[PDB]
Image (cartoon, rainbow over all chains, first blue to last red; front, side, top):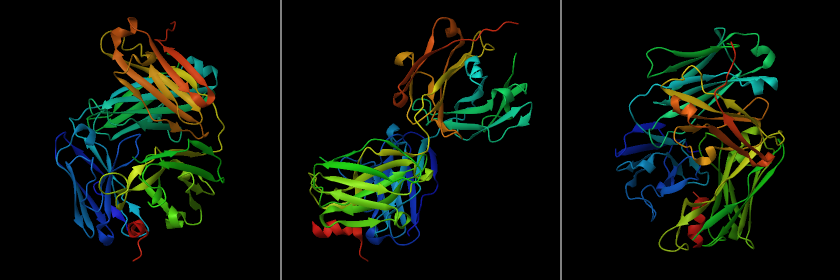
Amino acid sequence: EIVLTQSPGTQSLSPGERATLSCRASQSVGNNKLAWYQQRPGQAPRLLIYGASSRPSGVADRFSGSGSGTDFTLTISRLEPEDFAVYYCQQYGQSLSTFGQGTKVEVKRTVAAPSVFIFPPSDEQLKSGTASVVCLLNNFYPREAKVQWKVDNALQSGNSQESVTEQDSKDSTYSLSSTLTLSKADYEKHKVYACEVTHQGLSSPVTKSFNRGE
Amino acid sequence: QVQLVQSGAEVKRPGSSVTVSCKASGGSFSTYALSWVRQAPGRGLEWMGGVIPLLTITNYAPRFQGRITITADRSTSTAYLELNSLRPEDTAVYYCAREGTTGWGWLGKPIGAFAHWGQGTLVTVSSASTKGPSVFPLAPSSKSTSGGTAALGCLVKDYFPEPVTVSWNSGALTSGVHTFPAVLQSSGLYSLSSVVTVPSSSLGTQTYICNVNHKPSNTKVDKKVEPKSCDK
Amino acid sequence: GWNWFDITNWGK
């Protein structure tokens, strides 16, 4: 099996900048049958380059492919707003076709610390017997962020989940939401509920909390 | 013009087999290679295999050899992907994709690479039963009242299957809105949150209502979110 | 090497 390596997996670049994406094969790609695809969130992949350097009619000429053997490159002359997406290379130089793991090209922008908010469970949910505590990290950059749940200062594990939005099309930030869930009974055995946040844009952890029943 | 149309999303129990169809129109169904590619949530693309209808020539990826069958019905220009012994890890969007061609029209020389893609088909492998979500408020913090930015939202929890849509004030409010990807809880039910930040001063000159729609359970809630008032 | 991906080219 031919392994296609796409490194780095993420490139943070400025609008209008040039972009070069590398795709290296574990072994020679038959007849240079290497292809590149673009995929935006929620959409199906789209062919950009085939045969290592051929560009189908319709694809912007700012995209070009080069290389042969085991070293291929996808070049984007200048990044338009719609070019920030994920790029996959694929080899079909033999019956067993394979894709690389993809490279995400995102918008680089000034560091932005997250605005943190904590929400206690609604009385409506409490009546149902469960308690969900939510923590929101709003409009931060870069994407790397970490959330720790502490109840009465005890680190929580296995009772929370989170998800992150796609990069905002207007301000290029990310937002993250984390939910801590406990049964009503367990929720009422503790007092201080806190969400501790760490991010490149914070010189020290930011903690937001509330006290049950206050 | 080549258009590939796939069958709708489907929930499948573990151990069962799923069948996904892809109906083609335009170009030539019989003489171009048709492949299937899947993508698990948050993961990359993976070629599963393909078929050349004219001579029923199949080609499967080793990883799926023994669990997959790809067939093509030339009388309807429909290709089929069958995947057996389903496991939760098979939960993914499955796409059919036909080889592209060179030159004008859609009957030129085949290029091998995938130029035509279907809209994809989300296959969810789970033992969960359809269920409507409860919609709870994420009330604006009272400790922000005067001046500044306030955050509020809605918690849409315990629903199955995907998807759920959320809008604010019937679509009139979009600025500052963040509707997060759902998470799959240990119970096998989904949960998502939608939030919005607004000027704290607007908490008295504007109402906030999240409009939640979960078609499978016919759950359609318009939840008003306001400051919670408490005594003492 | 018999590339399944080259078959439709041969037939065309």
